[PDB]
Length: 49
Length: 48
Image (cartoon, rainbow over all chains, first blue to last red; front, side, top):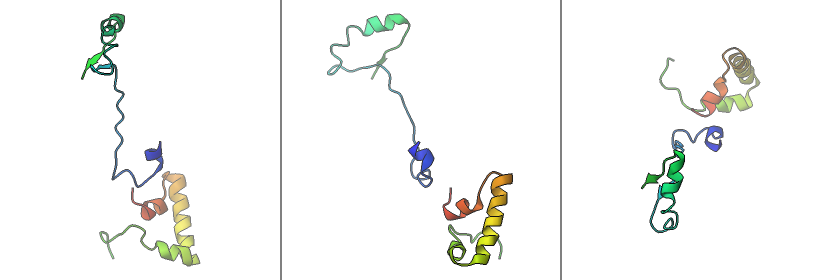
């Protein structure tokens, strides 16, 4: 909204919004890794890096 | 003169001082805003 408000920002900066889904890293998610298969059983997709 | 030398904020200093300049701009800017839904003042003042 700030970019849609401020007028002169258009030429300098464009905002590309990306929603990063479930993505499996080893360090932080090392607990979450085992249930990756479990969540994926709901017909949903978890992603590799 | 013709087109091509036009600059951002051209004659905008005159608009802030002269009364005759304001009447020309505002009557023009009002019409454009109502009929075509845009303002020439904004376009001249800051280039989109």
